[PDB]
Figure 1 (cartoon, each protein chain N blue to C red):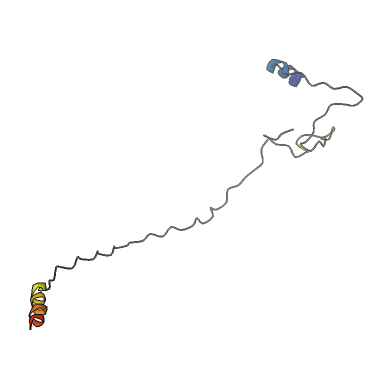
Figure 2: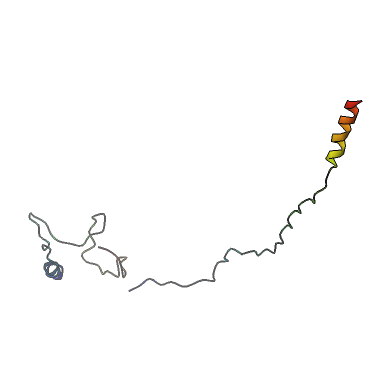
Length: 50
Length: 50
């Protein structure tokens, strides 16, 4: 929601897609993160990119 | 959240070595030693005239 909200202020189209599936966070290689564990459980720290 | 980092004893930097150098004194121009050219010029004439 905030990313789509911010995109519109920049004049960029919000994130949108069609077809069966879902939205989630992924690494640079496309691998999705675990949905049930803390970012402190995963190896995430200040300045990482997702 | 940030990763911890403890600073160890600094590694030895490459040592600088000074040098005291005294320059070579230049060469001296040879003073003008001179041949009595006219004497041998009269000589070859006298022996020739004989």
